[PDB]
Length: 151
Ligand SMILES: Nc1nc2c(ncn2[C@@H]2O[C@H](COP(=O)(O)OP(=O)(O)O)[C@@H](O)[C@H]2O)c(=O)[nH]1
Image 1: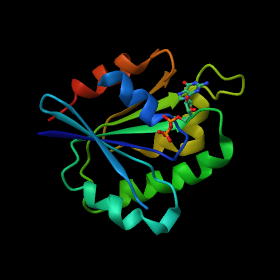
Image 2 (image 1 turned 180 degrees about the vertical axis):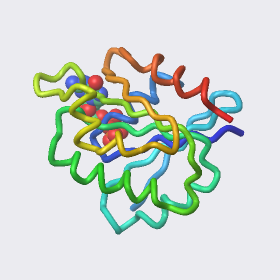
Image 3 (image 1 turned 120 degrees about the horizontal axis):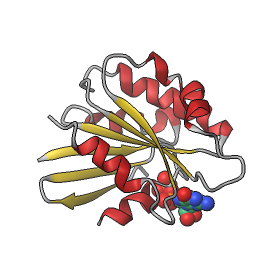
Image 4 (image 1 turned 90 degrees about the horizontal axis):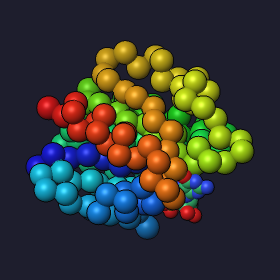
């Protein structure tokens, strides 16, 4: 099994995106040897310890961000940092979906990289792909980037 975590704050669009492909709550989506484990990083410390249990077997991460929500980008950055620093998270590829690129206030990848501090990630591959979860624009491109980097 190839395990891909699909994460981000609530309202980022992750359920909408993964639908295209096929207390604390998780959803599982199978696509052959790929298994997507999909969950929200909402609630801060309330459930964080639960979801960190999925890190050990993670082969890649899809981090979904609402491109148009600055406030939650603050919390998203924090949760991302917890993930990166966790001893069970291996140095596996991270695909960032800059989702809701259709919205007027959508931040472009350069702004998102700055907001999240992605340029400081130098120990594993990562890429930001703007996406529209409603039309599917960008989604296949992002998944293909990730799939070619599995090991
Ligand atoms: N405008 C716009 N809305 C989106 C996009 N992707 C998802 N949404 C909407 O954002 C809301 C939250 O989506 P959801 O998949 O439930 O996010 P989740 O909590 O991370 O799974 C839903 O109402 C979606 O219809 C997008 O690319 N553009």
